[PDB]
Amino acid sequence: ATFEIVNRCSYTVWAAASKGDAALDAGGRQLNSGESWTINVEPGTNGGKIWARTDCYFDDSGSGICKTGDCGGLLRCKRFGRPPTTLAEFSLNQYGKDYIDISNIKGFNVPMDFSPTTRGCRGVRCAADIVGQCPAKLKAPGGGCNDACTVFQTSEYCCTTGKCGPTEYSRFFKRLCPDAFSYVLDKPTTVTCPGSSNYRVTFCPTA
């Protein structure tokens, strides 16, 4: 499956793509404002994620650091990135279907649209200004808006025991972006697409 990753933001981002234990495609690449990078993701990829990283520096061997979304200091991500990170999430060819969603469970750094480029389903979007409206105690000094699990490390926010409910913090994310996961047990906003669909992830989809 092809995922065209497009940077409409006015600033550079470093796209990242991983399934947690491995890179997807090259795993990461710089995208200046306006650039597009098309990756190929193996069919049957389960638990894939794509995200943006901001204010990164890499040296000649591709080691450095990112202020949001850092995946162990690599340009080419092999693991998931450090919160806060708005997340495009997908599992492909799962009994004949693709499943896609956007999640704020690991916080928010960059607005995002995640849409099929082929027929038979709709896209999802979290493009509100969550960074600018972020509650005081969630603001990440490094840039972006942390989820409450990251900040407070409680069973209620992290949903450790599997029994959590919505919270003042999760409700802020859900109000800004009704169509993204705001906590682990949020009512699903996952979209079912035909197996082997193709996709576009757009950073900063709106003005």
Image: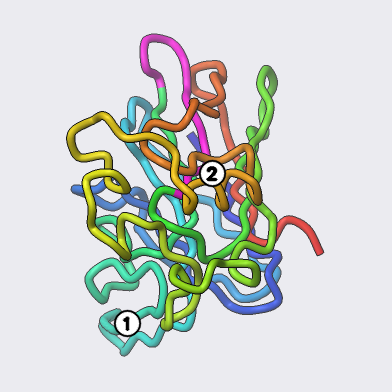
Mark 1 and mark 2 residues within 8 Å of each other at the beta carbon: no
Viewer-proximal residue among 175 and 78? 175
Circle 2: element type: strand
Give the crowd class for mark 1: few <14, some 14-19, many >=20 residues within 10 Å.
many
Dot 1 or dot 2, earlier in sequence: 2
Which quadrant is home to the C terminus? bottom right
Quick check: 99 above or below 166? above
Q: Which residue is drawn at 42% across and 64% down?
A: 146
- Residue indicated by mark 1: 65
For image coordinates 33% across by 71% down, the residue present is 70
Q: According to the image, label 2 marks what residue?
A: 3
Q: In this view, does 64 lie above or below 164?
A: below
Distance of label 1 from label 2 (alpha carbons): 25 Å
Q: Where is residue 31 in the image (x, y as percent from the top left)?
A: 56, 70
Nearest-to-viewer mark from 1 and 2: 1
Task: Report helix, strand or loop for mark 1.
Answer: strand
Residue 62: image location, x then y, percent:
30, 79
Which of the numbered marks, if any, corresponds to residue 124?
Answer: none
Seen at 44% across and 60% down, the residue is 85
Q: Nearer the viewer, residue 45 or 174?
A: 174
Provide the residue span drawn in magenta. 93-104
Q: Which residue sits furthest top?
A: 95
Residue 30 visible: no
| Type of amino acid at the residue the image marks with label 2 | Phe
Left or right of 87? Residue 117 is right
* Amino acid residing under circle 1: Ile
Q: Is residue 101 part of the magenta span, yes or no?
A: yes
Residue 205 found in image quarter: bottom right
The crowding category of the residue bearing disc 2, from other C-alpha atoms within 10 Å (few below 14, some 14 to 19, many at least 20), is many
Q: Is residue 161 magenta?
A: no
Q: Position of residue 138 (x, y in %)?
A: 45, 68
Most frequent secondary structure within the magenta stretch: strand
